[PDB]
Amino acid sequence: NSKYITALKRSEGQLRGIQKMIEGDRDCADIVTQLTAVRSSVERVIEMIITENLTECINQDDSEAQKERLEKAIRY
Amino acid sequence: TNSKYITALKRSEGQLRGIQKMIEGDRDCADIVTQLTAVRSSVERVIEMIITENLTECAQKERL
Amino acid sequence: NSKYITALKRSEGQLRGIQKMIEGDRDCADIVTQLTAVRSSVERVIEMIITENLTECINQQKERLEKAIRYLI
Amino acid sequence: NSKYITALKRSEGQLRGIQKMIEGDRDCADIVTQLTAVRSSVERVIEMIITENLTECINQPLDDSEAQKERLEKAIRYLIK
Image 1: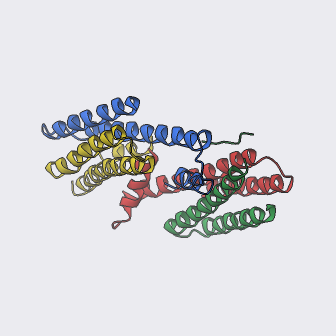
Image 2: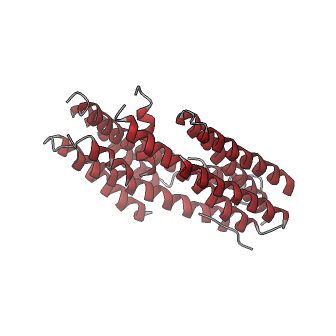
Image 3: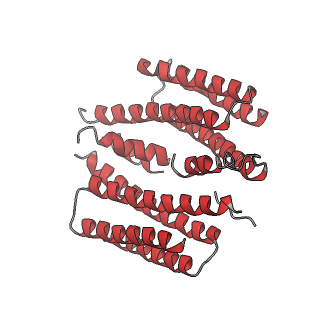
């Protein structure tokens, strides 16, 4: 649980860093590179919740477990 | 053009604080996945707007 | 088992058609959307084989558990 | 573009491979190992067409400037797909 808190705190702080870069008129490729890392850290939190939710979801839903399986095959 | 993207990332920054409050109060994790997917999409929208901002008047900035 | 002849044979003719489209020097957006359709239907066949594997372990045991650790590589 | 053609031929041919692994009933962790292999070869073809299209869009641009923002369409497909 609190793993996901600290990871989302990292993503929140990185978005504050990117705001300070846009304020500093930093280069748009440097902006896009850091925004890309934020996108990836949020997706990593999504992957970790869907992994944990699958591994208790098979020990038990309805047809929302196919969403979890769809997600894991698409990320694979 | 700066404050446009500042405001959009301030909105995403606060949505990540909201999702931390959702995790701390133990909500259904479909709701959490949906909100994080909205955060990822609003970040992707800012990426897309910045890239199509400069490549009209672009030298070289790229990404994968 | 023999449900999935048809989606895979469709994905075969789909990839043959993309080969003709690239041969026909046809538009790139059309080519990558037909390729994403291939990849999605192959993913859907993966998804159905995983899902009916996961139901078949329920009403009969490590076989659910290394199905779970398959999805997480 | 024969470089794409060889990889799509490998993809069709082991799709026949997966189909005739269903026509043995080979049990199915090995057929989804092979289906995963098909999926990732099609995805690395998709990524290759998309990058060399993107460097075609930037490096060899259209003479209509407003129609050269089909940069916008390849960037939106790059991001959300």
